[PDB]
Amino acid sequence: KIQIQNLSVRYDSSLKPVLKHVNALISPGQKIGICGRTGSGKSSFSLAFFRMVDMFEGRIIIDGIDIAKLPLHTLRSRLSIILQDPVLFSGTIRFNLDPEKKCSDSTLWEALEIAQLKLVVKALPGGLDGENFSQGQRQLFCLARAFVRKTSIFIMDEATASIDMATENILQKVVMTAFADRTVVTIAHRVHTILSADLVMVLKRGAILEFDKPETLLSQKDSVFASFVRAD
């Protein structure tokens, strides 16, 4: 569960604030994209809440807890993420698959067969024992490992930017049967999967343009996401 109060993002990191005065209630069972001129919209959400960068004003809260006393090791860990180039150690498959204590065959062939990587179970013998072909099977195993977090809140931002096109044919397909039934914010500059997302965001002026359904947005005579639809 998520409750965010009046968030205004100002960064001690580099010059000047970015996001300004964002307040809303958001729970699981949703999808959230990020559009705009300068990208990485969801990178502000990840960086703030998972504590990468820092903001100044406002808070993005989980349950009744706010950013203040939230457990640090919990906040930057219990979450999930997907990035463009997050390849991991190629030494051992079941051990990389076991960054934490244990999954073993259960989540191994369970999420592996769930990720289409079960043929990697057919080619390479049983893991803990890497062959790289493009990023397709590579980053497929990657974002598959990420999505294997399996907890309530999953986050991905522009994971399909470098992941090329027809991969989503399976890959977005994989998310189609996955990204549902939990807390998700999913952003792509192709934006194609943001259709059924209950919330959308595009960056103009100082902060996000607006937040609503895609069909409610395209429903008005004039709306942002429509205006960013043609030129893409």
Image (cartoon, grey):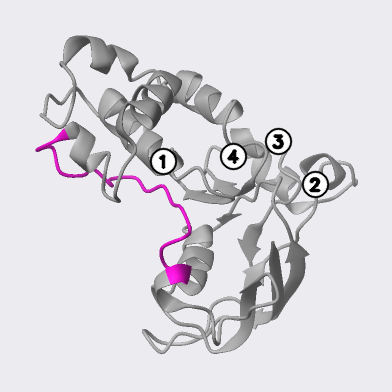
Give residue 213's mark: 2
Dot label at residue 161: 1
Q: Is residue 209 above or below residue 11?
A: above
Direction from residue 226 to residue 88 in the image, left or right: left
Q: CA distance from mark 4 to mark 3?
A: 8 Å
Which circle marks residue 195 in the picture?
3
Tell me where residue 29 appears, x and y as whole percent: 71, 45
Q: Quadrant of the C terminus?
A: top right
Task: Name the N-terminal-most of marks 3 and 1.
Answer: 1
Tell me how far mark 4 sits from mark 2, CA to CA: 13 Å
Quadrant of the frame with the N terminus: bottom right
- Along the line of sight, the residue nearer the viewer: 81 or 126: 126
Residue at 90% in and 47% down: 220
User: Dot 2: few (<14), some (14–19), or many (≥20) neighbours within 10 Å?
Assistant: some
The answer to the question of whether label 1 and label 2 lie on touching residues, with beta carbons closer than 8 A, is no
What is the crowding at mark 3: few (fewer than 14 residues within 10 Å), some, or many (at least 20)?
Answer: some
Q: Nearer the viewer, residue 17 or 154?
A: 154
Q: Which residue is mark 4?
A: 191
